[PDB]
Image (cartoon, coloured by chain):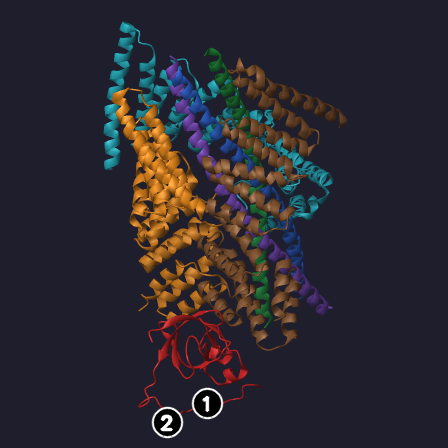
Chain colours: A red, B brown, C orange, D cyan, E blue, F purple, G green
Amino acid sequence: MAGRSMQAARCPTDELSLSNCAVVSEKDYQSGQHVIVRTSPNHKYIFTLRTHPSVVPGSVAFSLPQRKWAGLSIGQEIEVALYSFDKAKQCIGTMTIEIDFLQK
Amino acid sequence: GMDTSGKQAEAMALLAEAERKVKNSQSFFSGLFGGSSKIEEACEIYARAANMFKMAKNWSAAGNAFCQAAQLHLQLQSKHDAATCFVDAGNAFKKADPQEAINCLMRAIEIYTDMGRFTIAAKHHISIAEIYETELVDVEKAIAHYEQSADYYKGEESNSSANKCLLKVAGYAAQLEQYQKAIDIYEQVGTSAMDSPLLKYSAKDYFFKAALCHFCIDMLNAKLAVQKYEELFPAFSDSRECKLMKKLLEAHEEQNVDSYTESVKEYDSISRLDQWLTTMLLRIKKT
Amino acid sequence: GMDTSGKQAEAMALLAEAERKVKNSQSFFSGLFGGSSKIEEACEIYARAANMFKMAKNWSAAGNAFCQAAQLHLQLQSKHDAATCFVDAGNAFKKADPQEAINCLMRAIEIYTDMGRFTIAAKHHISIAEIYETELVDVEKAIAHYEQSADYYKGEESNSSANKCLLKVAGYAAQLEQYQKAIDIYEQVGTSAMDSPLLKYSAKDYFFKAALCHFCIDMLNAKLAVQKYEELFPAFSDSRECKLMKKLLEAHEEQNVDSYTESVKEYDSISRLDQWLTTMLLRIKKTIQ
Amino acid sequence: GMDTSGKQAEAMALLAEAERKVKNSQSFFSGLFGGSSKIEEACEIYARAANMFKMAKNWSAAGNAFCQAAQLHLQLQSKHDAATCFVDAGNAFKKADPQEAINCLMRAIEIYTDMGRFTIAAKHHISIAEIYETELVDVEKAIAHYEQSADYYKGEESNSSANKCLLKVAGYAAQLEQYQKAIDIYEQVGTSAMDSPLLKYSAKDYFFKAALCHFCIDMLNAKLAVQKYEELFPAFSDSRECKLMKKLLEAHEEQNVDSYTESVKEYDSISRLDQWLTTMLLRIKKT
Amino acid sequence: ALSEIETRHSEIIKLENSIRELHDMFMDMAMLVESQGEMIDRIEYNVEHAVDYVERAVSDTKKAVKYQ
Amino acid sequence: RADQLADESLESTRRMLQLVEESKDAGIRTLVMLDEQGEQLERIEEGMDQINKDMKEAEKNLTDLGK
Amino acid sequence: RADQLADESLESTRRMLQLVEESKDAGIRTLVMLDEQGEQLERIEEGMDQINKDMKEAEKNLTDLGKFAG
């Protein structure tokens, strides 16, 4: 809850990368848990956790789209704190999503 | 030549009469105990017999006589002379058989460290590191000796020698694929060079090497590292190093060997590359 | 490392032995009156323990032991050895406590310059200025130390070092202090180099900096000094700096910020700035109205 | 300010104590025969007083004290300390009044040459030449000192210092309408620079100056000298010097003064000349 | 245009001449400075050795005088 | 044949670039060694001063004791 | 438009010639001077080795004489 230092890692599986959830170790967190990844006092990003056995304890895995959106890189040290979503306010009713072809 | 082997033979005879001198120490010095100067001149004849051996092109015999003179000379007096004789024996043994040169150089190192001469100790440590590298294949011992000499030199504000030792160690590490130490050393030396106007222009190469060793380990952090070097040194992007690195890392995003192969061939078209950089590129760009 | 811990342990043992040795020496002086060999031996023990201790990765107490040995040696009417040990202790304290190093270096400077050696005193003054300005954020006493070093160097007709120190002092003055001293120093160094065997082609920069300071003072002074430099130094007439400064002056006269902007940007593009011309140029731009 | 005033006050006290010391010490030597330690102590007091006077920025009295200490010490039958005191007195007298500085430096030269050492003698000779040149106008004394220093340097095989002194002497001679000596010195140095792997690049300049100074006499001799120099150094024609000399020769031959001036102006535009060379060229244009 | 291009050709030939001369000059720079660096290194080593030896010489001579 | 001259000019430009780059590369290390030589030189100077002072005081004390 | 071509051409040649001549003249004097420092440091070596040998012999002779006296 207070936040603990970890290490950013690469996503282990393609499907988990597509799931857009931070892949974490079972020993460190649980699937469905939400975290806020802080790399600096002004850079905070919120993730949803998905557990995979291959994740070594002491690190958090992110996929390349995630490692590009969140400014996270393999081997870097990242502090992960659990995040609580206010369900009376933060439940997304309608989101405006821009879409485009990933591959030319 | 053989006129110098004849005087080498009579130098062996001089060593024989030095054996007679130690026999005197055995039997007759009981009444000549005051002949400490006799032992000193015995050591002197030992040393010049070793000199005649060296002139006779008997490196093993020269080193053996030098070390024997050093051993006979360290009678709790004139320790500096014993250390000088030991280093002379090590120099004589450098050629032919250098194994005992290593041990005698350690003995000189210990003597100097006890005395407090740090520059000489660090220089001899560098000497043993280079003899290991050129004679033996062990690098770890050479790395340790270079680091230890750098520590001595930095202890007395001799910054340049420590910087060069760390540079060599970092280069070997990058060739030995220890990239954290390589990147740390390269960035530290680049920042240190940036401090003074004299070495201000050199920071580009150090930044380039640090960026390469970053980019090998974690590809995504390569962009952040090159960016960070660029704002830290505004005249780094202008350098061909940064432009080339950006080209390679941007091409690697898409799997197209032609792009970065053409890039590297163009880079080699303007200036020949080194074994370290070429091997690094061939290893890294494979995956 | 075992070696470090053993070094620290044996250094403590040697320091305790040295303290007991000096106590027994002061006792024996009345007890037996052996002379002064005991005190010199105690100083030797202190020096050996201090050198071993600074080899032991520990610095502060090594410098303290060196200071104690130096004081005991100076108690024996020995100065140069004590002064050198003071300098070594100050160098050791450099990374432990700046103030102790500063005080020891002052003592060394005083004793050395009393002996008759000025070059070592000037070098110590330069070291003081460097150590002060590098870690402590202040200039004034650094300026004083640089001036003293330059004076000592000039006392023995060592012109190059004094000139370098004066140039640094003038640069710092222009950066912070008033420009009159900086203008005078820059003009002096520039005008003392028309005949330089190896510096025939850089007086232009000194005179250009002086002209920039004049412009930082006032436009009229700027232009008058600009001419003074023009006729004084014919080669400066054809220098690109001359054209650049004249263009900047004629632009600033008409109150057009665009011309000044384009001129400074082109000058920066063709050749890089220096972090001192840019600040003066920005201060000038602040007063375009 | 306060430091200088305090130094001067302490120095005045030390001087008064020094006169008291010398007087009472001579009295005690006469009445008790205590040796010479008191005289040496008085000499050291004089030396320290001179040092503190220099600290106090009083160079005339500091040099006077240094000279007094030198005289007292040489009166004690010792030379090196006296010579050092004399040269220190000269250095103090270098500014303000250097005439007595010149005299004391000459005394130092005399004692040094009495001992038998050369390098210091030549250095002092060139120093006196520099003093004459910078503070006086009697360039003839500077020429004589340069000649003595050059002779010493050449005799001691120090070819570089002798070459420098000879070049300065030739420049001064050609300045004072003397060309034969200048011609000889310049051609000698140019020939000395033939085989030099490094000075070969500079060998051309001496020959160029020699050709100009020789052309100060007449035309045909200049043409013969320049063609001889070209034959001696076949590549000399590569530089602009030979073409410039030939063009000036023909322009003077056909009384084409305007063409000569235009060519000189073009050369000045491409490379500015000095006062000496401009004076030589204008002198050439006079006829 | 003809005069300009001919002058540019003269300038380029002068470019190659000057640059090659400076390049040879610079390799000479490097050789000479490296030699001087080595020989000063040797002199510094000998200076340190002489300093240490003469210091211990004065020490032992003064101790011997005290023994007298 | 002006196009041939342009091609030759491009080749000469490339040659000049290569030569200048090599000269700069060697100049950087020339800087580094000059720095190293000055570093060693200051230390040797200080050692010379120390030995000279120790020697003056030592010889003077011995001569005074001789009397 | 050839006018500005000629302008940049004349600027290029002018700056090239002046700057190149500057380097060529400058290096010569420094490297003529370096040999003087080399030979001075030679003299340093000679005098210093003589000095070291002198003290070595003097000290050893003094020690021998002191031992003889005792």
Q: Which chain hosts label 1? A: A
Which quarter shows the N terminus of chain B? top right
Q: Amino acid at mark 1?
A: Glu
Tell me the tag on residue E66.
none
The residue depicted at 34 percent of the width and 44 percent of the height is C60
- The answer to whether residue D256 is visible is no
Side (left or right) of E62 relative to A16: left
Residue at 31 percent of width and 18 percent of height: D42
Task: Name the secondary structure under disc 1.
Answer: loop
Q: Residue furthest right?
A: B2
- Residue C14 percent location from the top left of the image: 36, 36
Ranked by sequence position, the earlier of labels 1 and 2 is: 2
Say if labels 1 and 2 share a chain: yes
User: In the depicted view, which residue is nearer to us: A30 or D43?
Assistant: A30
Judge from the rendering whether residue G38 lies leftward or rightward of residue E53; answer left or right: right
Circle 2 residue: A93
Kind of residue at badge 2: Gly
Residue D270: image x %, image y %?
Answer: 58, 52
Q: Is residue D86 above or below residue E4?
A: above
Residue at the outermost bottom position: A94
| Label 2 CA crowd tier, 10 Å (few <14, some 14–19, many 20+) | few
Give the alpha-carbon distance from disc 1 to disc 2, as whole Å. 16 Å
- Residue marked by disc 1: A98
Residue B77 coordinates in the image, percent (x, y): 49, 26
Q: Secondary structure at mark 2?
A: loop
Q: Closest to the observer: A56 or D169?
A: A56
Which quarter of the rendered picture does the C terminus of chain B lie within? bottom right
Nearest to the eye among marks 1 and 2: give it.
2
